[PDB]
Each structure stands twice: as C-alpha cells, then as structure tokens.
Image 1 (cartoon, protein in one colour):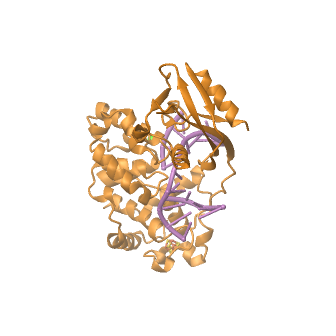
Image 2 (image 1 turned 30 degrees about the horizontal axis):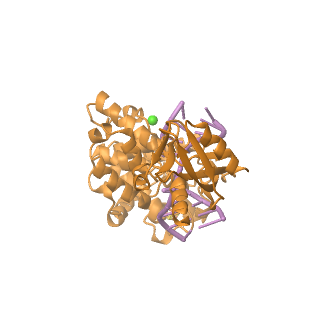
Image 3 (image 1 turned 135 degrees about the horizontal axis):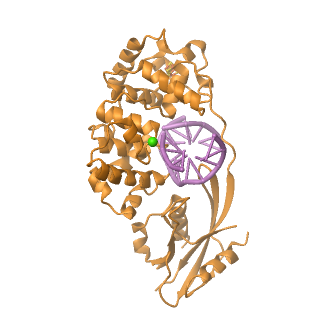
Length: 352
DNA sequence: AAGACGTGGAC
DNA sequence: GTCCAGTCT
Ligand code: SF4
Ligand SMILES: [Ca+2]
C-alpha cells in the first residue's frame, strides 16, 4: 500500500463512523471483560442476535470474577440457543486463568491474551484495540470483504497467505491514534454499507479509495469457496412421560452439543424399535412408544439432523440412572437444550 | 490441516 | 433457500 493515501482514508472512515456508529450494548464503555464477552458472542453470530444475549449475560455475570466463580451449568444455560457452545466453555476457562494467573486483569499483551482459550487472531485484535488501545488488527469476515474490494485482493480468503496479506494491509493503513475506533469502523462499514451483495458504494465514505469500485468488480469479491454439501443424519427422538415427569438425558462432555440436555434419541429406518432397545438398556426402565408425530430438519454447519419424534410412556421401578433424569414439565425451562430439542418439545406439547 | 463445531438475521 | 455473521488443535 505505498501509493495509498492512508491519512485521507482514515479521516473519511472515522468521520463516517462517528456519525453512523450503532448504539450497541457493549459500546457503552470499554471494560476489558465486557468487550471480551461481546467479541466471543459475536463470533459467527450477528449483532442483532447477540444484543439480548449480551444484556442478559452481563446482568448475570457482571464481572470477570463473577463469571470465573459461576457453575458451568449456569454459564451454559446463559448461552442456550446462541450456538457454538465451546465458545462459552473456552471463555469460562479463560477467565479462571485470567483470575489466577493475572490477578483478574485481562492481559494487554497480545501473546499473553491470545494464549487464553477461545482467543484467536480476531478476538485478540478486537479486545485489545478497544479496551487498551493496542494497534492489533481485528480482521473478521466482513473486514476481509471490505479489504478485498478496497485493495483488489483476488486470492481465496481462506488461505493463510491471504490472511497475512490482510493483516499487513491493516497495519499499514490503521490509525495508530485510535486503533479501536479504526478497527470498529472497518467492521461497521462491512455491516452497513459494503455488504456481500449490492454494496451501497454510492453511500460509501471510502468510495474514492476503492479499487473494486473503480474496476467495477465489487460483487465478484471476496474470493471464497462454495460450501460443500453436508451429511444428512436420520435421528429418532423419543418424548416419554411417566405421569407420576419427562425423561431427559445430558449429553457427553465432549463433541457435538456437549453438556446439553436432550430427549433420548438414536441415529438410524426403524426408529420405534431402535429407541425401545436403548431405553430398556437403562436400569429399571420399561417403555412402549406411539406412532411418530412430526419430522423436521435441524441444520449444523457440518451436518443436518433429520429428526423424527415419537411420543411414549415410561415405567420406572426406582431411580432413573445417570445420565438420565426425570423432570416435571414445569421444570424443563430450567435445563439447557439445543434448539433442535427445544423444537422437539414444542411439537410434542402442541401435538396434545 | 482438515474438518468439527450452532444458529438465525437478512435478503 | 442461500449466504454468511471465528476458533479448536
Ligand atoms: S465503494 Fe463499494 S465496494 Fe468499495 S468499500 Fe465502499 S461499499 Fe465497498
Ligand atoms: Ca490464540
């Protein structure tokens, strides 16, 4: 970027930003903890989705120390529905490490902050630039689009060599007087103006510096790979009631939807049979199912569940063995369920 | 490294 | 219906 009028670019970008910057809950102050939380929540999740989750989370866990001391169950429930749930296990671990190793002070050194679980190259830039003024780039998906257009970067943005290129662009053009403002403005541009399709280039404060605008190829950029097809996964789910409460179980601490509660379920096309062999395997449990009541798909980034719900009734001769639990209906909202199984419940509840 | 890892705003 | 808003190791 040797012929790039960085100072004029910065002026124009940061004058636009002060006029148009959205009033968002995590912009109300620059507390390193609250900034960090918002930036974890914001990973692969849109601002408007995050807003109510951030507000509730901080009401519940208002300080790094208050989060570090909380039970893992209450932390997970606070994330219920947001997706990519290891973010919150990682953040939880990271705040405990900050509390013990760093005295409850978020490290302002990039290497030390990035060593915390959950903190990748985007989060280290976003948190340190915003809370501490550190001039680290905060290159997210939208920034990569903006910079690919401004500087006509025609390389696949998934490559490390492209990422290094974007990081180098940002270091050359950044306003070291206000790196947090500069980083937020590039993101904000990508969100309200330089959008994936039909960018509002005529409304764009940096149109004069944009090579893709000049050559007329904004919409061919950035260069990404088409997403491959994802495995579809037949999943039989059983909603069982003893009417004396409903049978649920907690998932594994590892892997998909770890530590979330679910209705008993089995992968397969004889769902009625496969589920009966499973539930009976448990201690003192006897079950008989009903005809299915609904079938629906639930998508993940890497696979797609094809859920088939089966209602049924239970008969326990005593305690229900871990990992299983009996829960009165009234008490289900207390547990953390994936969205797929939240739907399972709503479909079974209206089915009556 | 590749692939695992959730969900829905915005259109 | 399709895109796309990051980190693990
Ligand atoms: S002129 Fe258009 S393509 Fe270039 S930065 Fe602005 S909105 Fe994006
Ligand atoms: Ca890191």
